[PDB]
Image: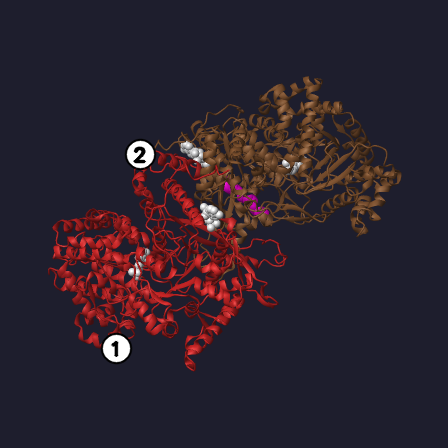
Chain colours: A red, B brown
Amino acid sequence: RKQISVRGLAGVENVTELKKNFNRHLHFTLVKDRNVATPRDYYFALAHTVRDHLVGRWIRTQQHYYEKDPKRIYYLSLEFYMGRTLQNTMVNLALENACDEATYQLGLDMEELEEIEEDAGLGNGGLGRLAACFLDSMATLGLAAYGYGIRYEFGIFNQKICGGWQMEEADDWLRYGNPWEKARPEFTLPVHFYGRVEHTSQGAKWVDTQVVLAMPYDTPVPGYRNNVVNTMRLWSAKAPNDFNLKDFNVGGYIQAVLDRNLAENISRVLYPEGKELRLKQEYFVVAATLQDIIRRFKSSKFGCRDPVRTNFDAFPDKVAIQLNDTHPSLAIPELMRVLVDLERLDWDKAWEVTVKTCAYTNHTVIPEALERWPVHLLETLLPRHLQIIYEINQRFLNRVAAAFPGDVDRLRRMSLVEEGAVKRINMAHLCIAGSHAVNGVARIHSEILKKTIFKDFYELEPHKFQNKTNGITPRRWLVLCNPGLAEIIAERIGEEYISDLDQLRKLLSYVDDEAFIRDVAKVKQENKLKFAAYLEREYKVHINPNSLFDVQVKRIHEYKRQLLNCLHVITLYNRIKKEPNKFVVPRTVMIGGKAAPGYHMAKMIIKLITAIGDVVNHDPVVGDRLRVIFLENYRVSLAEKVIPAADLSEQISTAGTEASGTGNMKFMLNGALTIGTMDGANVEMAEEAGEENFFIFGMRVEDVDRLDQRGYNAQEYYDRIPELRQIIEQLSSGFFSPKQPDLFKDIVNMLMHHDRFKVFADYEEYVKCQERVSALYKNPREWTRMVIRNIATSGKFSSDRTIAQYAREIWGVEPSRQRLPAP
Amino acid sequence: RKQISVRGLAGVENVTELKKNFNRHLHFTLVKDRNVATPRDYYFALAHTVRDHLVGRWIRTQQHYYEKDPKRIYYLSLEFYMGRTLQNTMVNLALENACDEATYQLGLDMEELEEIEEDAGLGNGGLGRLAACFLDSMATLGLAAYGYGIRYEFGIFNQKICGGWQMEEADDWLRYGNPWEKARPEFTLPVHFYGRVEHTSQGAKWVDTQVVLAMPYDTPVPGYRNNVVNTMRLWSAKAPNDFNLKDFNVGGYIQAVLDRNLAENISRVLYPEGKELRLKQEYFVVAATLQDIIRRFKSSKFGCRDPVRTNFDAFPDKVAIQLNDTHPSLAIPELMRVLVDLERLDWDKAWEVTVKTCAYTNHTVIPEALERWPVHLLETLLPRHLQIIYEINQRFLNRVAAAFPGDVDRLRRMSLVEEGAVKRINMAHLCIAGSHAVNGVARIHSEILKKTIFKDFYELEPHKFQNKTNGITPRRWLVLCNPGLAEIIAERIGEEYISDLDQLRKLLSYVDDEAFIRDVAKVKQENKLKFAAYLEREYKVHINPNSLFDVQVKRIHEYKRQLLNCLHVITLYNRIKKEPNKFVVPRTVMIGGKAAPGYHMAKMIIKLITAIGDVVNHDPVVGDRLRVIFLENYRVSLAEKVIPAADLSEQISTAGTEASGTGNMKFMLNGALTIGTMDGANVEMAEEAGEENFFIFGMRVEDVDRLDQRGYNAQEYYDRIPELRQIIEQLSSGFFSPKQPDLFKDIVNMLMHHDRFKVFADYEEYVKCQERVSALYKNPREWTRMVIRNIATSGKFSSDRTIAQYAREIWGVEPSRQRLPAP
Ligand SMILES: Nc1ncnc2c1ncn2[C@@H]1O[C@H](COP(=O)(O)O)[C@@H](O)[C@H]1O
Ligand SMILES: Nc1ncnc2c1ncn2[C@@H]1O[C@H](COP(=O)(O)O)[C@@H](O)[C@H]1O
Ligand SMILES: *Cc1c(COP(=O)(O)O)cnc(C)c1O
Ligand SMILES: *Cc1c(COP(=O)(O)O)cnc(C)c1O
């Protein structure tokens, strides 16, 4: 009977057993054959050849956690922007070299097959690109960690630039399956909605609820070469399917067609304000996921080690729930509904355990953006929960009162219930009330979380508030995407560095060396060529490989400032034009990002970018000195390509608007010099790299605050700054739009008359700051020289570090660089 | 690339290797582990170790067929009562033994695992077992045959008796997945619907349609020990899901949630009338299947052997289409459709092909059941197909007029358009006009086919009419469900009988060797014993293994006659009670059937046996001399159980009603005597066996037609017989009802006043025949020698015969029982 084991069925590295398991998977798993198989089959055969390995490990790893009994740290997040798992599972799992050999024999090119893979559409942006690094670093630093989210079938829309206009093409990545997940019908749990609270003798009962079924999908995550593979668990909604007659509800009328569908689309789609479905999604994921946690808590050796009712008395010791942005906050009242209505812990016992079990990483800098739901929305689909949210609140305000008697305005400033045109619930005030630690995500950002935005709460409980600066994984953002540059670097100092990133600091020691100079600039050369090429096979252009590579690949939005960036390109265009032969450096200026559907200004801004695009790039006198490029359907595996070929990172937001910034870091480590303003974490990048080593410019927060105070008038800059005057008049004449000259009319007025973000305010400095970079480009030695200084600096930006810190101050778990044994 | 082979994954009989592979599937496929695996997970581990051995073979067979390029025979049928695939994958592959040594060692009882598997809920009755049966033999006699039907998600209902009442529960057999099927998302086809035939220049176009997509699953089907595994490909309907934006349809209104849901349920469930669902199911599977059929055609080197059109002239030579019943009849206007509209064959050529290519099989005894669809549905949804059923009709009544110049009534009798209040297409007439073979399913059924229902069709084309007689398969129905009798038989005459069951005649030589006489009977007593255990362990009662186990397991219906069998179990009961003391040959009557949703009489007859039971079964005076049990939810996995264990075979239909009856044949092979009326398959069975070895009885057909001519006054029968007068007043005063006495009224009155099937006429001679049934039982030597004279004579009843008659006479290929190497 123990006879059934993991101990002999993967003979791992051998390029013989790898051909064996591939050919096995192609024929028997995939129930296909070489006379029929397409690239996509051979790719699936390869993904299972690498997947057999991963679950060897994963069964061992998990089983390990059941004996050792660690604190389980459950990351809740409604986005998980992973994006391709073949290559990453090969470099982390060691297997990279063997896979290339097996396919080489087999007559298949491995690289052909990895670009076959669809970006795991489970995330949309950085809140979920973050969560993803957090998942790989946690497992690398051997913590019994677990990511939890919803499965999205349709991800989040795909971008298509039709007519140089944005059409969101749909992304059902999943319509051929996913060789890395494993459905689990066996662990299908109810998520309840609507219903009615009866108050009954031993508390209450939440009766006549509608029910939707949550059904899980484990996908496993390897850690860099240490054999710990942990469990990402995504849920899917599947309706009750009694739908024909069961309950004698149907028959009468099949408006249950709508139960089936509405419920079924709690999994269908990631969002891109108020909606019963966003909130449906948010109750869904956290009900299900808490049902799981109570279950490994009750059984993981605790059906054994009960002493106290397999009690939650020891729940915060053993289990750790982390809230990523406000979207999971319903974990706080659900655990309080679960703990008191379902078991029976007295209210206080329950709360003690909630505040001890949770934490909340904040990603919002401006307070209008904190999630807040209508009480008539809460009281309709989550009735018991609104009761719980009202009682927590009450108790919080009694505690505020003991601590500040008579500051009556405090009581209403701090409440969970917000009065107004519509009485609301403020979800961040729920989390701070309900976690034992609140951390922001940037030096600067957690400061203002203390000083202005959460200050009353920071005054009532100063302990709670912490910092935990955002970082990249060195694996995906340094080795996968920048292989040779990982190489030349390891040469000089070891292999501990991809798992101990500030050792990059030893490269300091090479700043003047004309070897690591041509070295580093060689891998960058390689990189800019591979990327030179992709652009006219996937998509078509005419680069000049020599040129500056001005990259900005950010969510398209007003505060992010691709508008000033195009103003500079129009400036340059016209400068190359009026001075037809003037030696200036070249710059391939590429802006990439998806808009946000039915947001007119971001849809227009891309129209600007792909309007300049035709004009200047089909101007003769430009030739190859100026190039503008919109990167269509910019996503994680397009980051990995393009960040490698970056020279100049653009980081132009308005100061005070970014709460951190992760694409930022990614450019610094791949030897991409940042331009940018003093915001979010473009600041700590400066604290190590050195202010000189960084093109930090324009307004800081003070001057915007001071310009908001003295009234900002855009006309006044237009009338002084002379090439500005010129290019706005160009935009209105319909220079960049002969067929509808009128077309860009609203970008003009936006700027001219009503701009919140002060683009023109930082124009002036920007053209002269960008002139600093184009003296320096063409001082190639010193150019590279600052690029090395940059990389050695990168180290504090590894998720390794952030997890290690979340590990140490909040979670209460020590990191670990040990390799687990086995297969 | 040729290194991508089937060659090396073949440990086959190696128990060492089979255990290593159960293990790979539990840890790396199912991604589960011994700490957390359940019995189900162990079943699914085993379903996969074997599937390696199935699909390895299917790859070699399918390649084979394209290397050789055989005529391929397509069997479209809407029903495939597949019923449980593991032990039957194992015995046709010889792995039965090595799987139990490998699981013995791993500490898992194989029969346990075996009972975890759900029946393939792919069917409903006689017609779906016969399809699967033919299928198994199509494979053993080397036919390049495919099975094509509809994949029901939720089957047909599971039958559950509530207090005596049939409540239908549902059969979502697919609730945990199905290991044998691989879904083929890659091969999605559209089926068109509604739309509008727009006519132009060359020909017509069906424009503006609704499109549903048919998505296929493949399940390999293994022929006994010859290593040929063929294909059953079921289609699952799936709505296009651009419904969210595309078309611009939704946004305006998502009442399109209905398209999706009406589309989905072309597959959501089987039937149990003039439903557009029914008709959308029948058409679905036809449009879907003919696409793969012209696809394989145009591929299977018929690109190569084009010479003229990739000529559909040569199409019947490499294709065959079998319309098992009226249901795939749209296969004839649809093959025409593709051929004249899409290709551009002229009508006459195409008709030559659709006629040389289809072959109808009929299962009816009577005129009334023939499928007939109102023109207004064919015109609503299937507009182009209505126009071709009309030119086909139009041309046909010309051949008929030319050949019967002047008989007008024959033209209105052969018409494919039934006339009256509502205008129908008689879909059986279609099939005879497009097929080139029309065939019964028994000698007399085929006879009333050329003498009554289609005699004018028999007069216009005598050559098309055939007979082919149903058969069981000795692999499932003897080897698999009763290895015991199959062991005592295999020693005396050899294993060669399983592929050639007329070698069972040799058993006659041992009629008087008294070892076999007690061997045969040892097995039946062991069988009945095993099943008596089931009756106390999946549900319960108090059995007696020695009693005459009497069985009837047919659908519950008035003509199939279990109410006769009730009146006789209540005759017999009364007798144990007038004189308790007179020994009476004890019986355990078991009647089991699924009634039919919303058939009141059938719902009523079941509630009688679960009543007749409660009374006699509890009454002390009986002991265990007679008991009654209704078998809950008859289905192939129970038939494999109860048919082994039966003595009596209740084949009591009214004479003239039944056309063949596969059930009949299952009983004989498993050594059970038959009691029954001289209808359909009681005829040929009694003929190979001798009427002395059979318990034929009752109103012959002649007899019934006389009683009909004089008017069956049932009352007179009531008034001559006392033991009946007795049991009639019994029901009515409420003896078997008592809490609601009047409860059986509509049965008493049915019987007395409107019994279409003359249940009282066959009372007398039947209960007398049962008195001579119980005589023999009380003489086991001779009982078992009439059982030897029975088993030995089954031969004619293997489906390998029926299929051979079919390969050779209709499809036009010769069988092959040859071993194909593999793997
Ligand atoms: N009681 C247990 N003892 C050992 N390993 C276990 C146990 N329960 C679960 N596991 C392992 O942990 C994995 C995750 O378990 P679960 O927490 O049930 O999702 C399983 O796939 C097993 O590999
Ligand atoms: N042209 C071919 N040559 C060899 N094998 C083939 C060919 N076409 C199909 N097959 C095999 O037959 C199987 C079933 O083919 P199909 O008839 O397309 O369902 C495929 O999976 C292959 O294993
Ligand atoms: C890292 C990353 C980003 C980062 O955006 P920032 O605003 O720079 O933090 C965006 N998209 C993808 C796909 C990424 O991997
Ligand atoms: C063989 C079989 C039948 C056939 O029914 P008859 O009326 O006996 O021909 C019905 N149900 C099941 C489960 C069978 O296997």
Q: Is residue B72 magenta?
A: no
Q: At which x and y percent is residue B394? A: 58, 40
Looking at numbered disc 2 in the image, what kind of residue is underneath it? Gln
Q: Is residue B337 visible?
A: no
In this picture, which residue range is highlighted in magenta?
B278-289
Q: Earlier in the sequence, mark 1 or mark 2?
A: 2
Q: At which x and y percent is residue A254? A: 58, 57
Left or right: residue B362 compared with residue A483? right
Magenta span: helix, strand or loop, mainly? helix
Location of mark 1 (residue) = A706
Occupied quadrant, residue A648: bottom left
Q: At which x and y percent is residue B449? A: 67, 33
Badge 1 density bin: few <14, some 14–19, many ≥20, Cα 10 Å: few
Location of mark 2 (residue) = A105
Q: Chain of mark 1?
A: A
Left or right: residue B518 compared with residue B256? right
Q: Is residue B543 visible?
A: yes
**Cα–Cα span, label 1 and label 2:** 67 Å
Q: Residue at x 24, y 49 (%)?
A: A486
Q: Is residue B280 magenta?
A: yes
